[PDB]
RNA sequence: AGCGUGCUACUUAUACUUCACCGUGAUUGCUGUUUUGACGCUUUCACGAGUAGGCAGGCGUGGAGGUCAGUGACGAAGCCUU
RNA sequence: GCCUAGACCGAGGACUGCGGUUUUUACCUAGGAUGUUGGCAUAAUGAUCUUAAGUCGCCCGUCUUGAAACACGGACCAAGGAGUCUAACGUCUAUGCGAGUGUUUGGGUGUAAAACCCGUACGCGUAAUGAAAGUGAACGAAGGUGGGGGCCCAUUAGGGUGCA
């Protein structure tokens, strides 16, 4: 720009940040999010897919399965804010979801043998309970879309 | 550097007014008053209805 | 090295321990004062209610004591004001729109408010309104500077010689107009309120009696301040 | 320096500090000392009273050399004594032997009487003295010797 | 008022008490009770229009 | 921010303040001049007129004089001129003068890379 | 908008530094800026303000003024402080032994202070032997004796000196200065 | 969708409230850690319209003393150019 | 007292304060945003220029109570173009010396219009006033009184000294 020299008192040391008092507190999920609830995915690859909610992960995400055989939606995570929580529920008391966590979905195409086996083990119980509700498998296998004259501010799900 | 409302920040409210703790604990904001069920207007104050 | 940093930290910890221990008693004092103020507020209300009921029973009429305190808000801009009401508004420290001040009712101050009446909205403030004003928008004049009332130490350092040690001491001194009302109200920077949520009436610059906004609204000043603070 | 003048700061402003109505006309009010008795009376009467009129008598061919008579007071008279011998004179002076101060030779015509002398005799040679100057000189035991 | 203030100051001092000499503006009146024995309220109404010419 | 960390750089006005009627007449250059006319629509600030320079548009003192990379730029005319930027290589950058020859310009570029000084005009 | 009760953006109207660019006066201000900020002594706050004054605001103090100030009761051994020049007075008959601190001394003043057994020190030497100005006595020169003040506030019946280049019977003595020539004011 | 009148909600100025930044005025403190800037740094508050006009701080030009042992025929100065 | 929907903002930058909870560097929502995930770095992101759309925008300068005016100059462009210098002064500021001050009229000297050096006079100041003849500034600690910064003695207060 001009001919103004830097001065000796112009230090280059970067100060440390102050000690922050933003101690994190737990997430507040919606009351409609109960394990076994049928959810509608609003974004992503599986947008419009009706899926089963299984577990609340420690990442603040929801563990979800189609089931994959019925839907094509595998075990994966979704965000609670990109989900419509319907009123349909499935009894998931017979499904063991203890082993599922963040490290299970760690990033390393090819699919792990473990993940396929876990898919089958979870989906067996999911299908056993789904068969009880008539048309529930058909409902889950069908994509969701907004028809003409559908007003989401008046509908109950 | 930043003014915090004691009416929003409970910690600042207790910092400014320590009695707020007792006010909250005793439910001073919804305290009942004990008295008898009376009606003292039966006599000459019925001059309000007509004259 | 950190020898000194840790040394001054230990010295600070000891001094802060002693300071907090000493301040605990003062905070007990102000706690007791606030509790006493609440007791006397409730006692006075029940006494007045009982007196009204008793006057109703004994074929009489209880006339309330006239209010001694008023909150005055300048709701008019700074243009086209005659010299005398302009000087009066300056002397109430109402030198901008939506500026509020506490005034102790006498004759001199009453004739002042009557002079500024076409330009202000005023009334009788309740205790909760006073508390809300002082808590959210309460500022003090310290060395001609506008300082937020964020700690009871500011109030003590400036009004302890007037026996005001807490924000509740200040609120009590305003509400029940005390022997040091002058010092407490001049220490209070004029409250700078926002515009009302919900608006004014259709036309401000006419008396409250005629459907406007200026003059004495008396108990509706609490609703108006609730709108604006 | 021209770079410091206010002429440089008015560049770009239309009227150059002279006003848009008043402007900088040639000679409004006249030239020099014009109008001193009619429309400049308010200036000359307030700040230079006595300007108009004659007072006193003329003096054809006044030679100021005639009136040369510089004044020296008494508080400055001992400064004419030699500096290296002032302290000795202030001690040993008596009626029998006092310093001689030739005031005319230092360029003074009249001795005036402001201030106070040391209570010490002096011999002052002057062309003129005031009444009080000689009274003060005699009081300290001194004398005035007239010269020309 | 100077003499009266001086008189008030000396006598409170005699009684070993205090007295306040600063003048005050007129203050709002206190509470009070209005007796209605012999004074039951009389109801008034605005009167109709008449011409008296 | 490869430079010393700074707040986000804010430029209050990014266009050029163009003199009034520098578009109507060729004799009127775009270099900003304040209108002094009695009737000027711009001097009286009518709605719809051009923006004018004022101190409110001044840059934040923490991001003032910083190029988009976060450095303050210093003009260098010879290799000895780089000596003043020795202890400020993370806060000051060097810009080579246009009239330095193609020979000396290569030498200036060579010393800055050894010293770690960043160069703002590296190709010309 | 604000209804301003005072003029906005008003400078204090007092000098906070010398107009002089003398580097050695700046050092003296350096010393008493620290002293006034840190001693709670009112003397140091007065000296700091006095070092800013302009030439006409620090009139010279004659060696006769110091003699009269030392002649106050109980002030014979006080330290005389003059923020300015101390000049000589050849109308004195005698001068005492005294300690005087000044910005400058004339040749006669230094000669006459030291001849009578006194000291002529600078203001920095004062700050070590009297860092709070203990046992000091500030002396100021006459401000209203300046010739320019003769013409200040001139007007009718004001008795001030006219702004005039020549003096004599022919120069502003006739009309308005004499009842025989109209009126006198 | 006119006239008189009442009510609920709503619209938006460079005005008001909270916050950020520029400048101006004031303000807190800063030398046994003053430490190669005290004509400097720093804490805090309030304020910002303007013709004629005053003052201040800066930008630019011809030439001059000093300095960069400065740039330059391996290209100065000038000129055109999202 | 409680629950709940949205928006905008995140200045500051080791620690220091007040609280609160005390789980007595135990923490905290308590003197200003952190944590975590994805994507991009041949780029999501940002600026300018041109242009479209929307909205607003009358020709500048001047004299003028009032100008876009049916008031005047101005078709366009380049270059030149207007508060200067001097004699004598008022106020203010800086500087040198100071009851004195000013070397530069002149003289000495010189590496030659410079720089360096010298002194008598003179100007102004140090005395005023009166038309003039003329006279010419201490009763007193160079005065008293009420204030008066600072300083001294004190011990809220109080006393002493008190320049401008
Ligand atoms: Mg299928
Ligand atoms: Mg008030
Ligand atoms: Mg407290
Ligand atoms: Mg609304
Ligand atoms: Mg409304
Ligand atoms: Mg309206
Ligand atoms: Mg309307
Ligand atoms: Mg009505
Ligand atoms: Mg509100
Ligand atoms: Mg210039
Ligand atoms: Mg200007
Ligand atoms: Mg102008
Ligand atoms: Mg023009
Ligand atoms: Mg002018
Ligand atoms: Mg003109
Ligand atoms: Mg004129
Ligand atoms: Mg005539
Ligand atoms: Mg004479
Ligand atoms: Mg720009
Ligand atoms: Mg122009
Ligand atoms: Mg026009
Ligand atoms: Mg106009
Ligand atoms: Mg070139
Ligand atoms: Mg404003
Ligand atoms: Mg104000
Ligand atoms: Mg005097
Ligand atoms: Mg004179
Ligand atoms: Mg006559
Ligand atoms: Mg209608
Ligand atoms: Mg604004
Ligand atoms: Mg302005
Ligand atoms: Mg130049
Ligand atoms: Mg030239
Ligand atoms: Mg040169
Ligand atoms: Mg930050
Ligand atoms: Mg992840
Ligand atoms: Mg457009
Ligand atoms: Mg014209
Ligand atoms: Mg005309
Ligand atoms: Mg005009
Ligand atoms: Mg006309
Ligand atoms: Mg017309
Ligand atoms: Mg005309
Ligand atoms: Mg004409
Ligand atoms: Mg024409
Ligand atoms: Mg032409
Ligand atoms: Mg044409
Ligand atoms: Mg002059
Ligand atoms: Mg010469
Ligand atoms: Mg002479
Ligand atoms: Mg002479
Ligand atoms: Mg006295």
Image: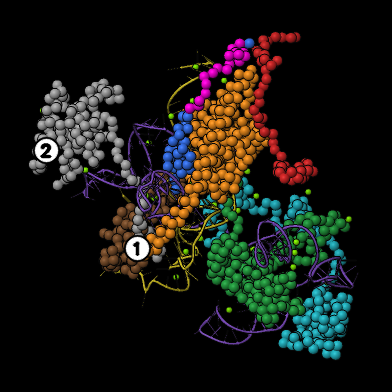
Chain colours: B blue, C orange, D cyan, E red, F brown, G green, H yellow, I purple
> Is the residue F74 above or below the residue E5 in the image?
below
Q: Which residue reaches farthest bottom? A: D96
Exactly how many numbered labels are in the figure?
2
Q: Is residue G80 visible?
A: yes
Q: Nearer the viewer, residue I53 or C85?
A: C85
Q: Residue C185, image x and y in percent?
A: 58, 41
The quarter of the image holding the N terminus of chain D is bottom right
> Is residue D1 inside the magenta stretch?
no
x 12%, y 25%: residue: A131
Q: Which mark is residue A118?
A: 2
Read off the magenta span: B32-50
How much space separates mark 2 and mark 1, taking CA atoms? Answer: 58 Å
Chain at numbered mark 1: F
Magenta residues: mostly which secondary structure?
A: loop
x 52%, y 44%: residue: C29
In the image: residue C107, left or right of residue B9: right
The quarter of the image holding the C terminus of chain D is bottom right
x 61%, y 62%: residue: G42
Q: Residue A48, image x and y in percent?
A: 19, 30
> Is the residue G123 above or below the residue C152 in the image?
below
Q: Secondary structure at mark 2?
A: helix
Q: Which mark is residue F88?
A: 1
Q: Secondary structure at mark 1?
A: loop
């Amino acid at each position: 720009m001009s001919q103004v020299a830097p001065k000796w008192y112009q230090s280059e040391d970067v100060p440390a940040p102050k000690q922050t008092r933003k101690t994190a507190r737990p997430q507040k999920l919606r009351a409609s999010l109960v394990p076994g609830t049928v959810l509608i995915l609003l974004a992503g690859r599986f947008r419009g897919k009706r899926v089963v909610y299984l577990k609340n992960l420690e990442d603040n995400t929801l563990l979800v399965s189609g089931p994959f055989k019925v839907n094509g939606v595998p075990l994966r995570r979704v965000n609670a804010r990109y989900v419509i929580a319907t009123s349909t529920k499935v009894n998931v008391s017979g499904v063991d979801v203890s082993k599922f966590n963040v490290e299970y979905f760690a990033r390393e195409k090819e699919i792990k043998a473990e993940r396929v086996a876990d898919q089958k083990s979870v989906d067996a119980a999911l299908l056993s309970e789904i068969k009880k509700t008539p048309l529930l498998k058909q409902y889950l296998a069908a994509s969701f879309s907004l028809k003409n004259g559908d007003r989401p501010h008046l509908l109950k799900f | 550097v930043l003014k915090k409302n004691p009416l929003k920040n409970k910690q600042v409210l207790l910092r400014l007014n320590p009695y707020a703790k007792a006010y909250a604990a005793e439910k001073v904001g919804s305290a009942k008053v004990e008295q008898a069920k009376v009606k003292p207007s039966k006599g000459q104050f019925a001059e309000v209805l007509k004259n | 090295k950190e020898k000194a940093q840790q040394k001054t930290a230990e010295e600070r910890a000891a001094a802060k321990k002693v300071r907090k221990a000493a301040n605990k008693e003062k905070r007990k004092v102000i706690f007791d004062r606030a509790a006493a103020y609440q007791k006397e507020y409730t006692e006075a209300e029940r006494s007045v209610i009982k007196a009204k009921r008793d006057a109703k029973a004994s074929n009489s009429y209880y006339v309330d004591a006239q209010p001694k305190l008023v909150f005055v808000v300048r709701i008019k801009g700074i243009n086209k004001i005659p010299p005398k009401p302009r000087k009066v508004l300056q002397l109430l420290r109402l030198t901008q729109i939506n500026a509020g001040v506490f005034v102790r009712l006498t004759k001199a101050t009453s004739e002042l408010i009557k002079l500024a009446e076409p330009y202000v909205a005023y009334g009788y403030p309740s205790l909760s309104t006073i508390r809300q004003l002082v808590y959210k928008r309460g500022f003090g004049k310290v060395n001609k500077q506008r300082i937020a009332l964020s700690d009871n130490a500011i109030i003590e350092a400036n009004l302890g010689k007037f026996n005001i040690l807490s924000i509740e001491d200040l609120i009590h001194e305003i509400y029940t107009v005390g022997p040091n009302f002058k010092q407490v109200s001049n220490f209070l920077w004029p409250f700078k309120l926002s515009n009302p949520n919900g608006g004014f009436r259709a036309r401000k610059f006419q008396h409250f009696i005629q459907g406007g906004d200026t003059g004495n609204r008396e108990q509706f000043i609490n609703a108006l301040v609730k709108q604006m603070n | 320096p021209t770079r410091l003048t206010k002429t440089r700061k008015h560049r770009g402003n239309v009227s150059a500090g002279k006003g848009r109505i008043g402007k900088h006309r040639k000679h409004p009010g006249g030239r020099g000392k014009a109008g001193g008795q009619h429309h400049h009376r308010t200036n000359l009467d307030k700040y230079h009273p006595g300007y108009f009129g004659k007072v006193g008598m003329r003096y054809f061919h006044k030679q100021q050399n005639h009136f040369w008579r510089p004044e020296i007071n008494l508080d400055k008279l001992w400064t004419l004594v030699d500096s290296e011998k002032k302290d000795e004179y202030l001690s040993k002076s008596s009626a029998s032997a006092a310093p001689v101060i030739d005031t005319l030779a230092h360029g003074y015509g009249k001795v005036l009487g402001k201030g106070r002398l040391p209570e010490v005799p002096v011999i002052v040679k002057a062309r003129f003295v005031s009444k009080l100057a000689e009274e003060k000189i005699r009081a300290v035991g001194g004398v005035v010797e007239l010269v020309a | 008022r100077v003499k009266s203030n001086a008189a008030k100051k000396r006598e409170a001092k005699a009684n070993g008490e205090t007295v306040y000499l600063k003048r005050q503006a007129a203050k709002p009146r206190g509470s009070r009770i209005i007796s209605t024995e012999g004074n039951i309220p009389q109801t008034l109404a605005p009167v109709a229009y008449e011409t008296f010419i | 921010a490869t430079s010393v960390p700074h707040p986000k750089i804010v430029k209050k006005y990014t266009k050029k303040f163009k003199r009034h009627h520098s578009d109507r007449y060729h004799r009127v250059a775009e270099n900003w001049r304040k209108q002094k006319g009695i009737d000027s629509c711009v001097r009286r600030r009518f709605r719809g007129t051009i923006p004018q320079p004022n101190i409110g548009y001044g840059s934040n003192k923490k991001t003032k004089f910083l190029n988009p990379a976060g450095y303050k730029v210093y003009l260098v005319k010879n290799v000895k001129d780089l000596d003043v930027l020795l202890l400020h290589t993370k806060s000051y950058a060097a810009e080579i003068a246009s009239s330095v020859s193609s020979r000396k310009r290569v030498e200036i570029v060579a010393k800055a890379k050894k010293l770690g000084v960043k160069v703002t005009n590296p190709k010309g | 908008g604000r209804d301003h009760t005072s003029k906005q953006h008003v400078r204090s109207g007092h000098r906070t530094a010398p107009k002089s660019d003398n580097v050695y006066l700046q050092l003296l201000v350096k010393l008493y800026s620290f002293l006034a900020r840190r001693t709670d002594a009112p003397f140091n706050k007065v000296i700091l303000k006095s070092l800013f004054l302009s030439k006409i605001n620090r009139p010279p103090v004659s060696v006769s003024r110091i003699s009269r100030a030392l002649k106050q009761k109980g002030a014979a051994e006080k330290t005389i402080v003059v923020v300015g020049t101390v000049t000589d007075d050849n109308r004195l008959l005698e001068f005492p032994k005294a300690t005087i601190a000044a910005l400058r001394f004339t040749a006669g003043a230094k000669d006459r202070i030291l001849k009578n057994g006194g000291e002529a020190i600078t203001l920095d030497q004062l700050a070590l032997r009297a860092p709070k100005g203990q046992n000091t006595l500030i002396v100021r020169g006459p401000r209203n004796s300046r010739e320019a003040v003769r013409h200040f506030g001139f007007g009718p019946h004001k008795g001030k000196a006219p702004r005039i280049l020549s003096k004599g019977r022919k120069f502003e003595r006739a009309r308005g200065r004499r009842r025989s020539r109209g009126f006198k004011v």
